[PDB]
Each structure stands twice: as C-alpha cells, then as structure tokens.
Length: 164
Image (cartoon, rainbow, N blue to C red; front, side, top):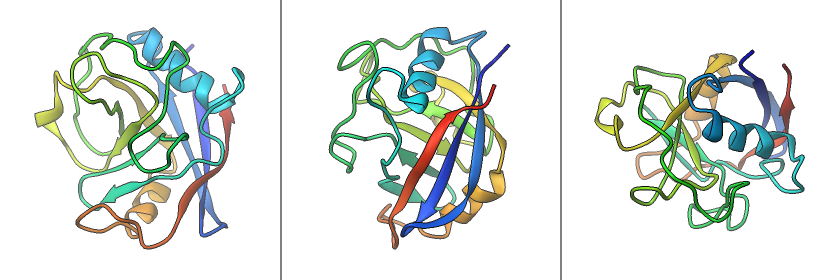
C-alpha cells in the first residue's frame, strides 16, 4: 500500500540514474503525503528541476529547496511549515529519508537522504521513507559532495513522480 516515488538524477545535465523511495504512509501519513505530492507535482509545484544543494560524504544528501535552491526556501503542500508528525521511526542506517527543519514543528519541503547511521537525529527529525532501489546512485551522488557540503557539479532532479 505504501507509495513508491522516483527521482531521475542528473549531473550537470547528464543523466546519472534513478532512485526510488518507499514512503511510510502507514506510519507517517501527513509527512509521506507531502513528499509524494511534491514528487508528482500534482498541486502545481514540487521537486522537478530542483537541486541537491548540500552533500556531505559519509553523512547525507540534502535537497528539496525548490524556491531558493540553497537551503533557505521550500514549502509544504500544507502551507509554509507543518508540525512534526511523530518520531516512530529512527535513523538506522544509509538510505533513510528524513525531514530537514529549523526547530520544532518547522517542516517544509527540504529532506535529506542519510548515507550513514545518524542516531543523534532521532526524535528531532521525522523519518518518513527509505531508498528502495538505486542506493548505488545515491552513493554516486556522494562523490560530488565535499566536507562543507558544497557540490562540485550541479545535482538536479531532472524528473520525478510516482511509480506505485
């Protein structure tokens, strides 16, 4: 029943590969629905064409700022911010999909893909999905990151949507 969405990733316009995510709508429905709708664009705005603005190898890939492209923008389908839904799920290893925020109850559209176990984020960021296919593409994206998070090449979501 849990939806699966995909991103097609491009490096400097050149196709890199596809990553698919399972969204845990069974446990975090409001959070999962936000990501799903932003991935299909069905509300008229969303992730297509946006970049991953912060990539720290051995830590995570961060994206979802489709309004200022640098970590200061984004918005949810529910308004500018929405609440922390729950902290049922934990940051247990690579492939976890979790919400970025600016403090309690500040979720918008930014998210990060963990490329390591990040237990210190438990109870502070809402985990809502995991990589299903293409973890190897995430590992490839990592090689364009750096210690301070700046990317050497532009990593963009060339296309995205729902598979199931």
